[PDB]
Length: 537
Ligand SMILES: *[C@H]1O[C@H](CO)[C@@H](O[C@@H]2O[C@H](CO)[C@@H](O[C@H]3O[C@H](CO)[C@@H](O)[C@H](O)[C@@H]3O)[C@H](O)[C@H]2NC(C)=O)[C@H](O)[C@H]1NC(C)=O
Ligand SMILES: *[C@@H]1O[C@H](CO)[C@@H](O[C@@H]2O[C@H](CO)[C@@H](O)[C@H](O)[C@H]2NC(C)=O)[C@H](O)[C@H]1NC(C)=O
Image (tube, rainbow, N blue to C red):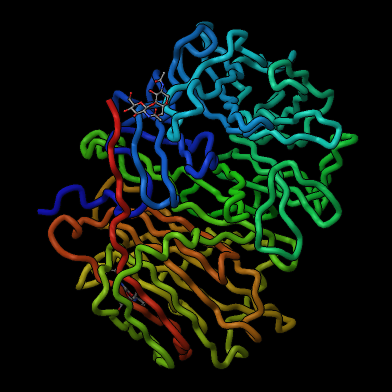
């Protein structure tokens, strides 16, 4: 009997209890700070939520500290909900977050460290005039929250967006300020969308064109595009566009308003929510954090004593084509790599399963690249309006095609009674144009009852004719993060196989299609544990 088989070895999570939204991520004086919605009293959401706090020098190894922000004033007496960090000139980190006041309404509060001499910024002081911002005229008391990191315009005026909705229409309410204390709502929202519901944890930032670097939030210009991100209808959506400080205008590149449909982009197509990014000027990259909810039952959570994980932090940038974002785990993760097992020029015949020996199958970093033959044999299927997730749930690893399913079997039992299959399928429309589907088939990830085993999928924007299909998987016990085509398509999965309680996991490569596929190259590394030190009480 293995203890806590579902706890991860290198993903961030508190010692125990419930954790959701990542809060105020930032880099300050050489230290990476991470905060998060935390329930000090249970492994479920609760009436009292506070900001947990941890610090790190590399985003991999962490030191758990005492919570940083917890109810101490009327403006946040019932709870301290999500917010973001902005480092103001003069080198002072300012935290804006949504507090639940004594009247149970959502208001925006300000706090900043009380002891800048402390490398870990443990103590925080709250502004005497909180709340700084209260719900606009026609907005309900519980539909106004999650202030973003602020950006300073060329006119010396600060901007921030706060999420909410006006009559069920998602809103990114824009506020302005020069002293960061007195804020005035701009006449029009920065962006919005009809019937989406409250926009949660909005994020607004620039990305450099033709570059894999990150930018400080306040950069603007012609060689820069902006990303408007918001969570609603259960997922995190984003759209790339152009921002004009002058008129506070955000113009979507594709001219669409978010609808939460297969028409819009997401950072990740699996369990991924309340994502928040920050600029890291030490490495000149933008890092993205995201809450990964549990998919087991609440009773299971209370039983194991904890709930919620954070995705492994990923660098973020805009693709060469400028039509979507690219994500990739921060390079620091590579330091966890131990022994390596590699394969090259290996054919995977139809219906075959190849086991990868010598790897810690429950805690690994696996990359594989497939070279295809006989593309003309791809099943004919126009995918213009097809819902990729629906398609993966309809056709799992057991549904045999021509090109596909071929990919990986992770967190699998020796007898394959339980397995999580991450794979691809290749289709072509009537005109001979190819499309690529990436799937995380979780239908057989566990034999346990009361586990949400819904599968996830998304189309990958690559040309199978000229580029091999690559896949990287971060396997860490109850979480699997899959990156297709170098980060073009990401899918995070939560799995709870029963076998992990008594036996070891296995890793396989497979091809259940009728066409042959070749592994041009595969690299697998056992990953050692990240260190988590407690410096509390
Ligand atoms: C992909 O290749 C096979 C394509 O179907 C798939 O076969 C599995 O095993 C048999 C077919 O050989 C079938 O199992 C059926 O019978 C069992 C009896 O216990 C039922 O429980 C199943 O639901 C099903 O009716 C299925 O076709 C399939 N079984 C399943 C779903 O596990 C292979 O499993 C596939 N290979 C991989 C690596 O996924
Ligand atoms: C402000 O932060 C500094 C830096 O952490 C604190 O100073 C340290 O305090 C501990 C405990 O008293 C000592 O063991 C260290 O030697 C101190 N180091 C430094 C840099 O002086 C300081 O105590 C904090 N101030 C307050 C009000 O708590």
